[PDB]
Length: 579
DNA sequence: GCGATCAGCG
DNA sequence: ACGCTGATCGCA
Ligand SMILES: [Ca+2]
Image (cartoon, rainbow, N blue to C red; front, side, top):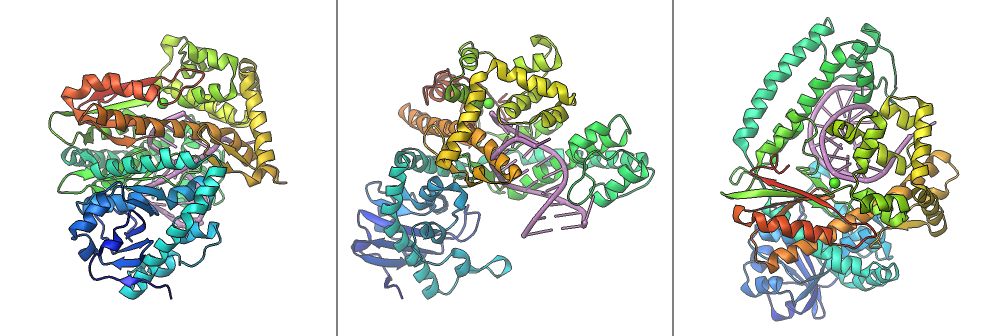
């Protein structure tokens, strides 16, 4: 129904200096995945190319790698990475419809061309799920059906660039697309393709030791419970705790008794078994998610894991990381932290370098709220998390453990993002009356933060959305909801999203500036991971001293705020040691 | 497939 | 009854 040329060879009119390009990778994880078909739409017509002909054609490969031949695409990182796995470089992507839709409205959840096109009343393209099917039925359709689908997707991109750019421009987001998110997409593609090397010998030894400890603890649990059961069965775990042993019920779920860690910790005075259950779960989590789960996704020939950073998923502008998630590798308990010993440089005599913004969202908050006291604190480079731990636990600076400071961190963020006296009292195991007074004291020291929390909710009501420093946007329809509980969740989103989102904007700019600086200095150092406000690199040991000066400076100077930004950084033989 | 749970970032 | 996530697991 849509006209196109099913081409048998590449012709010069397919190699124009502006085109919509589709390089179709159907598998969810695009690492080392098949490219099933290619479509090109430009001024001269519409073309479908089989990958075996197009990607072996030297002129088509050259066109893909020529940055002066501009391509408009949807999810260009998926294409870039799949092409890297084919030994082909993609350059010249000047418009990514996925990132444009994400910026316009992240709540749309746009995950294919059809969903983006619907934002602009364009419906002459099918959803990918209607074409490929779902689950066990998923399959590449017959070539004529595939070709028309890929051509229709390219035609949609070709038509949709201008109205998406026009709305981006009206939102003050066109530079956010072109100078931040699209350059970041190329950097993430390099990081994902580079991967992180894993010490599978050490990981597997840890797993064998874990399984022994797990059985020991499992037996002591059966013995403390007087009987055996399925320690992961709620119905059975609930029976043991809250019926057999008759422990108090502090919380319910929609489905029954709650056994979350906060509940178990409050029951520790009543019975030894709850601490064993906690230890059992923590070891099991390491075993299932971080030993077995990681070994599953290691590529055996290179011993590398290749995450996918989802750049158009979170509602605040953060990235997320999937299969494996390398943004939640354990660190806080020593037993879990040892997992990071398995993350190693990819070459001999290279090292891992990790750099982290200090108290990033409080510094962003001080800038946006213009709170005199919070700005003065960071101008003094005070550690507000430590200062809050001193006050909470009534200790001196010297006595603050990493654990008190971790807890004080949740108090600081809890309060500025709208925690109630009830929530605070439950977190600190303190009186509700004390919790409320401490919150009141907190806002006496930082009245500008209070004013900002009030103003930003009003602004979200008037405008219908909130923005970040670099003009990311999040619509909050529920902020005028008549339902108190629904309105309240929206109000805490108005409080949090501009801060968490501006911190996401800053580190993204930092990554672009860092990559350019590393290229300027002709260093071999390169990014491996981003963990929200931390950057993890690897480099030859001979570059470490230059990186100690280069990286903190690039990160500190990415933006200029009313308070300084501050970067902590370490390096070492494994990720474990980069602290 | 979903809810609880828990690993991380703030 | 602070916010943003992803993986595993049992299923009340
Ligand atoms: Ca930090």
